[PDB]
Amino acid sequence: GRHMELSPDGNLKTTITIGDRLTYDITCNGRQILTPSPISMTLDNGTVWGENAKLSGTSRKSVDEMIPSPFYRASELRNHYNGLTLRFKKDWNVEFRAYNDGIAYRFVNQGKKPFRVVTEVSDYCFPSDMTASVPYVKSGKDGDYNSQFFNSFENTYTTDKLSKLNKQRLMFLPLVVDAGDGVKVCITESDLENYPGLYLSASEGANRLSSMHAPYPKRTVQGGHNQLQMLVKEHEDYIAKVDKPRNFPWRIAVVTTTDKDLAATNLSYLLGAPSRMSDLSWIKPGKVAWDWWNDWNLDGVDFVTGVNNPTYKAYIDFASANGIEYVILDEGWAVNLQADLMQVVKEIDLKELVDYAASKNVGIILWAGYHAFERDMENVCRHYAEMGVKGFKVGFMDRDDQEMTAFNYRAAEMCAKYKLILDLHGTHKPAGLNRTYPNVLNFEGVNGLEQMKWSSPSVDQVKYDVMIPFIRQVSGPMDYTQGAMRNASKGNYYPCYSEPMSQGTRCRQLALYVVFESPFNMLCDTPSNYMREPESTAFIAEIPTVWDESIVLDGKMGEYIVTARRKGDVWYVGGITDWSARDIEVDCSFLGDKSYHATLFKDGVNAHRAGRDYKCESFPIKKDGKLKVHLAPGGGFALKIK
Ligand SMILES: OC[C@H]1O[C@@H](O[C@H]2[C@H](O)[C@@H](O)[C@H](O[C@H]3O[C@H](CO)[C@H](O)[C@H](O)[C@H]3O)O[C@@H]2CO)[C@H](O)[C@@H](O)[C@H]1O
Ligand SMILES: [Ca+2]
């Protein structure tokens, strides 16, 4: 039983073998980059899908279609693949898809009788000791996987040969394996609804990454961060309940021959479940005059700053004067330790604030800890939607067992029902959720700029920035929360909770608004700092967060990336580099034939010594244009062409 499937361009092919085990491999341009890798699902009735599998039928199709992708990187995304469905006896199938830039598969339940998934095998067997770039689970102890399942999915990348990885620490997704000769494999998953998230492990075999899933929770207890978390204390002997026919999540091996194709791949959105929303007209992407990063630390005002009405009114004024759409009331507005979103601290009047914000063309987003939000979800959403609140930022889930991934979707739907937008923090990679419910405008699961509030200088944020466009961002949008006006060149960074800075240059921060995808996007710094920086603020306030077209012009993972994005007849280009100074050329052949005006923010000539140093230039340009830009260490540039 040997089945082959090829990508439309013929460069990628997978061979599926049906024997004692069910396996698939991956060949790229003749070279085998994944050796036969076994897949299976073990059920509680002893049935193991994929061992001694009995094929009952097959079907093939060739698909080339455009998938609408609102509130994202393009108006629509191309879905172009050869598909193979293997139908087995006992009412289960496995679907394979071959794209030019990846192989993906998923199990499908067509059984009528409820059951449980005990474990799932999803192995990745490589032919040699390749170099992996992986994000380890940050918390917990080695070998104690239950201590690791409780984590916030925020960490930097460790780069090591497969044989050199920690064999006792889980890695979350996405992660990358360097297959050599410029080929990258990026492993991720999508359509992660009501199913535990997949970790990979180096614990089994040679040159092999194998799966592990958090077990279904048997007993959860309120605790953790300010009594807003539900901690798994006991777990079942299975990982998932299955009560109905369903698709299971896609297992995705992105395969690219150039790093810019990795950053650009659409596979995560393409393989998310289709939108479940008819009316999208009420969803408004945009930016936030954020309170939390900058620690409410305004200067030049006549009131004491903090979680109080005059402070939020100042953020609202600032947002409004600059056309910024939203103000978040972050953690602090609800009475601490009560986990009760109906108990407002005495220094705050939500009604006053929501109404004041409304009279200033500003929407209010309320922050909520997981348990406070989940416990009376529908009533909370109704009550605040009625008050005029536009959405929620929900955080500290720190779980990806089945119960929590079911909660993400349930939360998204409940917010959708009441015309509320949703931002998920203390969560994992998006894995398709923003396609299925487009009102979920951002996701954390990223070691973002908040880390500068407490991180030792050993944390290399500049390096991290040129890793995630190729790794974490492959899964979906990031709430990274950039926009620092305080910028520290190499050696000048220190963690400062109430007056934080970024690592690298001013223009790096500006470039991130193009480089990073964030439909719901922060201005992390104080209004005070922004108002001392008119030029920077104007650029940030004006740039779209949602795009009609996106092109990654060039890049090398962990070194640099240059990205151009279109909105109407306006283009933006952003570039960033690692700690090496770098010279970049921008080929402007993506432009139309009209004559255009460019506005360029580039690193100042002393940006290597003073991170804040920038230069803003104006000049005419057109399609033949080939703009040379110098990037300082930890620097970048931001370009607008109108
Ligand atoms: O990681 C070690 C440091 O953690 C700090 O605690 C942070 C935590 O790291 C962070 O993920 C979390 O961020 C969420 O909540 C915030 C409000 O509380 C914001 O909403 C933020 O956007 C959201 O991602 O905040 C924690 C603090 O609340 C510790 O402060 C630090 O000492 C280190 O232990
Ligand atoms: Ca966080």
Image (tube, rainbow, N blue to C red):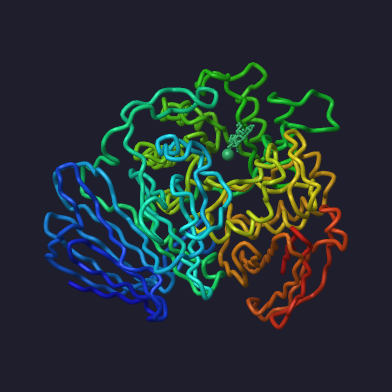
The reply, left or right, for residue 401 in relation to residue 263 is left
Find residue 258 and report its image quarter: bottom right
Q: Position of residue 58 (x, y in %)?
A: 18, 69
Q: Residue furthest bottom?
A: 624
Q: Residue furthest top?
A: 346
Q: Is residue 406 left or right of residue 227?
A: left
Q: Is residue 124 left or right of residue 442?
A: left
> How many marks overall?
0
Please name the residue shown 83% across and 29% down the image: 301
Q: Establish if 335 lies above or below 75.
A: above
Q: Nearer the viewer, residue 107 or 572?
A: 107
Q: Residue at x 61, y 55 (%)?
A: 545
Residue 579 lies, in percent from the top left, at: 73, 59
Query: Residue 583, how many percent across, how many down?
Result: 75, 72
Near-viewer residue (439 or 290): 290
> Residue 63, position in %: x, y?
33, 72
